[PDB]
Length: 114
Length: 114
Image (cartoon, rainbow over the protein chains, first blue to last red):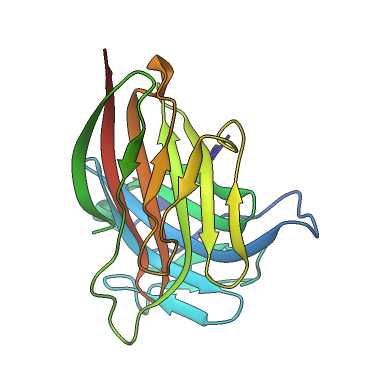
């Protein structure tokens, strides 16, 4: 019960897109430690962005000045990816690291239209 | 980028196996927030055990009597799994949630013999 396959997003070259990732339903007994956007491709994943309720926001290249958390909370890891291009197409994983229940990862496919 | 270790394991039925998992060297910039163990079986992830440096240890069913940390640290999530059943066959993933680097995981395939 780890993976939660979500929507499928369709964006456009040049325009930005809103990738969605929220946590529901939040319980007081469950504590969210981190939200982590990763891009999966060719069978290999890649760290994209991380929101930590205490450590702040981190964006990793090539996604700095591109990816921005809209409502950075522990139940919301929604991001905006700027300047879509053909290389951006692929599977995206938004993972919540929670204690003591474990990790919940949402999974969404992104297609880039021309 | 997120997968740094890929190994294999073997063991007889009823015997105990020590699944190793560690991180070195975490840069002084890098902070480990949580360590998580997962099992992948026929396209489905399942949370096993979690060690959070600031919250403690949690062993989830049905592993609450079989799986155990040996030296639980922010750089060591090595566990022992006792009473190996045939169903235990498969890939096990030990994940380090870090900031600002993100997720760094180790995958090991445990095969059951007799």
